[PDB]
Length: 246
Ligand SMILES: [Mg+2]
Image (cartoon, rainbow, N blue to C red; front, side, top):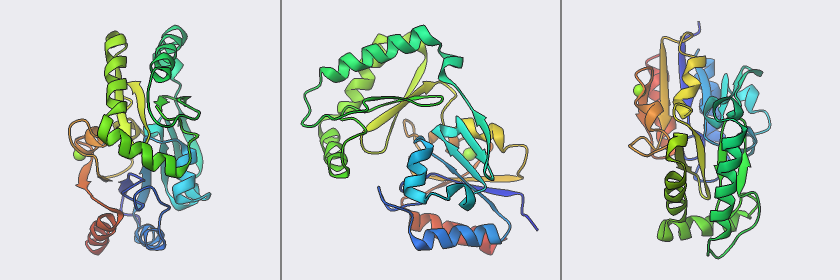
């Protein structure tokens, strides 16, 4: 029967090659785990659209749980089970204050490329991109390199932290071009409230598992058995072992 065991995965770098679609062997492994009685889930700091892009249009069919924006938008077997609102935690006046400041800081930057969708208001979070989410893949690659050198995202977060220390927001770098901003506690552990009562074990797999990494809280949550991975191949090999010990 069903194992009452959830396998919860990061997307980019955990289920996929870096900034690429999931491969055929990843899809096969997932189906084998599901075939063996495990539930499988995604969790990412990115939006649902991004998971569709890297995993497929039928992502809700492939996974038991899909947690976008850290579980601030949550799906269970095709059903939307939760959708949080940043207005609920922060409220209009503070949001407007925050996005205004962010826009000025971005406008002041001197980076080689800027495009569009610098401040993205999601469900329960705001995502902030110095270059803008509307840049091309090649532009993303180049901003990532640039940011490695010049730490543009870190400077920006530093300035935002100075402007708004009382806002109590967390700033979480992730992927090539942006960082997420959300209330303390709306990190990836947010999704666990939706599964904790339904599994005897929850295994988490991710790569950014240390202090300041966007997988730190969820890795170190007492509710999860953490598996630090460095690639989707690492993920596969560890899931093979979990399947073997059924
Ligand atoms: Mg844990």
